[PDB]
Image (cartoon, rainbow, N blue to C red; front, side, top):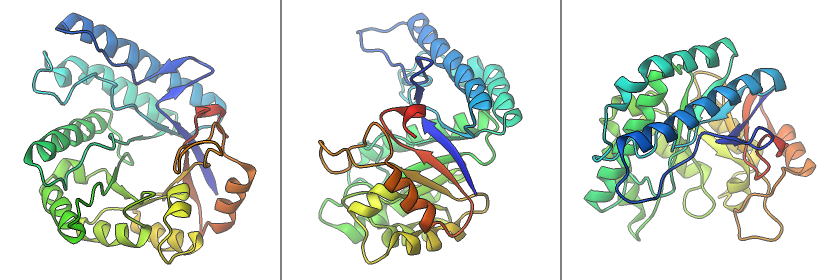
Length: 277
């Protein structure tokens, strides 16, 4: 019925795939050491998951820090192809399903050519990384992003800018968000691009449109060739709308389990990570 996962890092290990660098004038060697630490921790996390009943993991965008930037100082695909092949082999042997979820700021439908350009470079890196890991059921999850007034044209720019992106499209799935795009709207975009829909339960509660959760899931599930994916989070009782609690509540778990039309892979999004259950 259900498989489970968590994103980016693991708290009990103190392992993370998401280290970056801030100091000025970075050197190739400083970047390589940070990438090495993120890669070693990805291995630690795959092995931990094999042992602890987790089949899913979202890799941090920073795994190879600044890999999509023009200034990235060496050929990361060449440097890491052998290591990524081995890590991908481990993930397949452990039956783990891998994903990435680019920043809020990756915005292929932006009216600004420089934002679109940065955004597509980040998606191409993410999709290339999943290919190098040999992540066949791998997913690259994306929001529909800003409206900028112009909400029909925004969705039009998004579809247009992505439709030629063959490698991105191999893994791309679209997600509803808490403010701008509900499941019904995202369904329409997903259809245009020929990709699946990931329902985020908390975003759906915050921004449901005219669909009950059970109906959202019933409509989104057939958009998958493989097992459908759902994102489960709980609203933090003290923070702004959409902020995740440290752990998912029994109530929200039970609400999803009741709503489910069939088997699903559930990505748990909580501050407690693997402790977020």
